[PDB]
Amino acid sequence: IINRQATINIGTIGHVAHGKSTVVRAISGVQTVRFLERNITIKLGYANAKIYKCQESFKSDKEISPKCQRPGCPGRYKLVRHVSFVDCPGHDILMSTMLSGAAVMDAALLLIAGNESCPQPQTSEHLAAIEIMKLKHVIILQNKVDLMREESALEHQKSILKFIRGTIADGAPIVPISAQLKYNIDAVNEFIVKTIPVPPRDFMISPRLIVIRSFDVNKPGAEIEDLKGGVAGGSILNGVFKLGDEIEIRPGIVTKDKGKIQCKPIFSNIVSLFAEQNDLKFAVPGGLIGVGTKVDPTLCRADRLVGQVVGAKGHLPNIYTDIEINYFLLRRLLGVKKQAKVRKLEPNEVLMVNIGSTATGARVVAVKADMARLQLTSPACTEINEKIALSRRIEKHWRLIGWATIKK
Amino acid sequence: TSHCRFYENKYPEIDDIVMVNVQQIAEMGAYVKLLEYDNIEGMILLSELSRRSIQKLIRVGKNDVAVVLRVDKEKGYIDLSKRRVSSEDIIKCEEKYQKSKTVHSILRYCAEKFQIPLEELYKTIAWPLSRKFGHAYEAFKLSIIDETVWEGIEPPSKDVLDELKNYISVKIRADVEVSCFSYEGIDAIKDALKSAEDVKVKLVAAPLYVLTTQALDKQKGIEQLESAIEKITEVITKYGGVCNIT
């Protein structure tokens, strides 16, 4: 078996205590770490998957196990692609992590249960978000199908079909698969091979890195001096890294808390890399890699720096405080249990603007008809245009309004 | 089994002091067992016991200081007196008794260990210590400070002796919180640790470092810990990091 790492990212969406983690487990082999010291930093889940060919009726394709025995052929599998999974929870309070996950993702999998409530706005909202964030590769999957009646499922499918056609996602495949009884995943695997292609990626463009998770390597058992460096789980979109480069977290931090601040952002060199199971040399983008840099084990532990941009020495981007946004509004609101109508923008009110992955608070000053000027409270960086989703407040918690683009 | 005399000989002399533990009173006086000179009974008549409600007390547990009058060194008969003992050397006598008790206590591990008669063990112990030196507790103390009495006798059980020695033979905690922001960190932490060690140091989770400092003579503790804290403070401020001490 060759040690070729991740190439393309696939994600999973749903609801709490429904069936996403179970699905992930079914897909993979080794159990995940996520769900204070271990794993606890962000609500996002990271898991891997295998694409192995064995082609030497119509539906049979490949087996997840390293050695296939169930169909018949005892031959050795062809290496085509290795993939990394990002698990994102659809809880009503926390969605920043989900948003962050979306930015790195290039394939989306929808999972809704069968033996519960049918019309849910959250799923629709998720779909809308997917449509917005540069995606056409949408696969619909049904979770709990085994505890369902003979025609009810069919009816549900029909209803779904009726619902979904007038969207950005054109020819979306719909597959019903069980996660608790372990069946029918072959079809899914086949689909994964068929529908999803690989976009071009080269060494030319300057590196862009996003760190979601943070880890510390301190476990009880050994004596006093048995220490390892701080590991930062960072996923790459474009820009290849080799061992021997300086990694920096962009926004910066306060040095004394009186006294003026002028200290540059935190620089760190790579000590030990963690990919799939163990160590590797080259970092091919399109996967979440636990990069172990010279950042403190005391710093990376809790909710302090979740979802921030990472650059390299040599190339310099720009940091902004006043942001410029062009907005597009929707007809009626998404993600509300009954539906409510969208009001026009009002001056002097706290609203949350999500640019790419960051969750930041913004205040409205001057809006004519298309352009919007906003004031930031927590630091944020700007590169090109980014995938922007707006969130406004009416009652209790956050609600989506529409999509946005930066004009410069 | 508990037997064997405290001194070298079985039967007491004239004018010597003994401590008695009372079992029963009335009719005769107190024909009771001794805790200074063998477990065999020694008697006082109802006259020498008191001087100055007399019958109200003296039952079980209470100790009496008495001087030996008449000894029959043939079969086993002891006579005692309480009135003659003056309150000038009584404290000394008490001290002696205490010492004897301590010695007896010391001779128990051996009895426990090799499952052999206690009297023989006592005899083997008493030949270097109780014979030449005088009193045994002081000799024991001397031995524990500077080995001087154990030279005269060969040990059938050295392990037991070692155990005894061990038997004959204060941890203070400190809190340090680390939360850096500068370039280098792990190395700095290591350096800090190296300035607060010298015995037992352990790691718990992530932000807290727990060290236990051993005290020589009770009061000592602040005279190193504070210095260590100061050193730590000196360490972390230069680069661009903050640490807190509660």
Image (cartoon, rainbow, N blue to C red):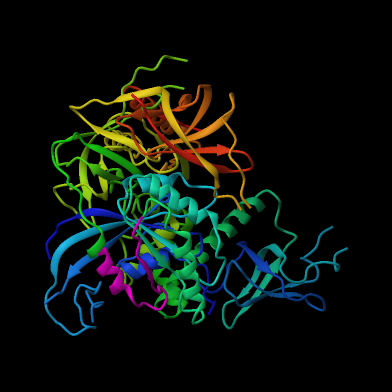
Q: Is residue B197 visible?
A: yes
Left or right: residue A273 versus residue B46 is left
Report the front residue among A39 and A230. Answer: A39
Q: How many marks?
A: 0
Residue A219 in percent (x, y) is at 35, 53
Report the front residue among A348 and B153. Answer: A348
Residue A403 in percent (x, y) is at 44, 39
Report the front residue among A334 and B103. Answer: A334
Report the front residue among A330 and A42. Answer: A330
Q: Is residue A187 magenta?
A: yes
Above or below, A353 relative to A285 = above
Left or right: residue B185 versus residue A2 is right
Q: Is residue B108 visible?
A: no
Above or below, B122 relative to A11 = below
Left or right: residue A312 versus residue A109 is left
Q: Is residue A15 magenta?
A: no
Quarter of the rendering containing residue B36: bottom right
Residue A25 in percent (x, y) is at 36, 67
Q: Which residue corresponds to the image point at 46% horizontal and 27% vertical from the top-left?
A: A370
Q: Residue pushed farthest bottom?
A: A72
Q: Residue pushed farthest right?
A: B53
Residue A245 in percent (x, y) is at 17, 35
Quarter of the rendering containing residue B239: top left
Magenta highlight range: A170-192
